[PDB]
Image (cartoon, helix red, strand yellow):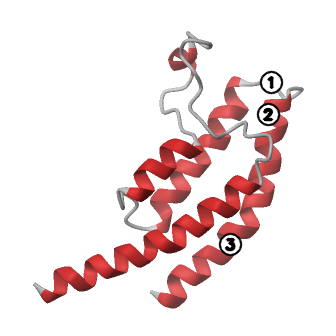
Amino acid sequence: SMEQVAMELRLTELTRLLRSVLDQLQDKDPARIFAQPVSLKEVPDYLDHIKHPMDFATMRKRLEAQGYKNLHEFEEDFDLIIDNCMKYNARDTVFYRAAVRLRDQGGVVLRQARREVDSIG
């Protein structure tokens, strides 16, 4: 149907906007701490601690499959990256501190993304 096509164009355009958001958030992680999944070879107990692992490469795979229907879904995955790290790692670690700085810096990007998503529809 033509309606299905229009819906698909909306999804494609959301995917465009979320790709730009993802790039901007990942720039706030210049150490690349959150770039890839925590390795279960190197942290064998990780899934005993963290039930839903997340990282920027995993988000990018979902994004490119147009697997985010709305900004809320995308934000959920970004918050997992931060929240998982702040639980597994102690306050005094470079990992925890990186997550705090990512959260704080990412807030700005996400605040305007929300206005753009609502604005453009």
Which SS class for mark 3? Answer: helix
Contact (Cβ within 8 Å) of mark 2 with mark 1: yes
**Which residue is situated farthest in the right direction here?**
92
Tell me the amino acid under the disc marked 3.
Arg
Contact (Cβ within 8 Å) of mark 3 with mark 2: no
At x 72%, y 34%, the residue is: 86
Left or right of 76, for residue 3: left
At x 56%, y 10%, the residue is: 45
Asked if 30 appears above or below 66 in the picture, the reply is: above
Which SS class for mark 2? Answer: helix
Tell me the amino acid under the disc marked 2.
Tyr
Mark 3 = which residue? Answer: 111
Left or right of 67, for residue 87: right
Mark 2 = which residue? Answer: 96
- Quadrant where the N terminus sits is bottom left
Distance between mark 3 and mark 1 Cα atoms: 28 Å
Mark 1 = which residue? Answer: 90
Image spot of residue 63 (x, y percent) = 44, 57
Label 1 packing within 10 angstroms: few (<14), some (14-19), many (20+): few
Asked if 11 appears above or below 59 in the picture, the reply is: below
**Which residue is situated farthest in the left direction here?**
1
- Quadrant where the C terminus sits is bottom left
In primary-sequence order, the first of circles 3 and 1 is 1
Using the rendered view, name the quadrant where residue 68 is placed: bottom left
The circle on residue 117 is: none
Image spot of residue 113 (x, y percent) = 61, 74
At x 67%, y 42%, the residue is: 82
